[PDB]
Length: 180
Ligand code: HEM
Image 1 (cartoon, rainbow, N blue to C red):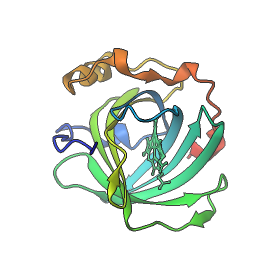
Image 2: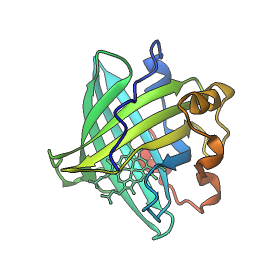
Image 3: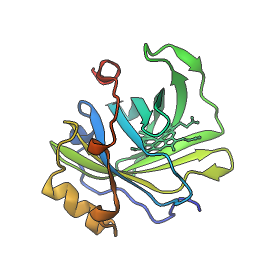
């Protein structure tokens, strides 16, 4: 199960609303049913003159482990979308593994406002895709996305009822790592 070839970013999205503060994934939808583990994630994306760099955190709620990354790539000209290479870092942002250039993720922003966002992520490791991942984001963990962001979910052809809500997973975050 590959990522969809029909994802496009929303036009006219204010990149300012997206490359702001820290995001928490409040809801996620992974199209690949072969997965078991559920995750929490938070990240802090930043942009300058078309270059994006972001600090990323995952907590595996099933295995109770965590990992940290730094992603970097270039904004597409076309709309609010980038393919990043990523390194693996520790919680102090020291590099553990430099980027494997055969791996990337492409993040497409589908909606963004002052409180909330919807993005699609296609993670690729070499040959293999992880499959489509949609994440509803908010700045305040365990907050509800805005009506605008909820509408984007439906307009992406999805149903919010099918997303996993992270606020009930027993997530452990590292809010030190995502601040600034
Ligand atoms: C709750 C939301 C998320 C879920 C469920 C999820 C799920 C996963 C899973 C299952 C993996 C393991 C990949 C493997 O085993 O090789 C992974 C790794 C990864 N994810 Fe996510 N993810 C989430 C959020 C995000 C976000 C928001 C981003 C990008 C901004 C992202 C980027 C990555 C990257 C770069 C890896 C590391 C791949 C590697 O180690 O080579 N993820 N994620």
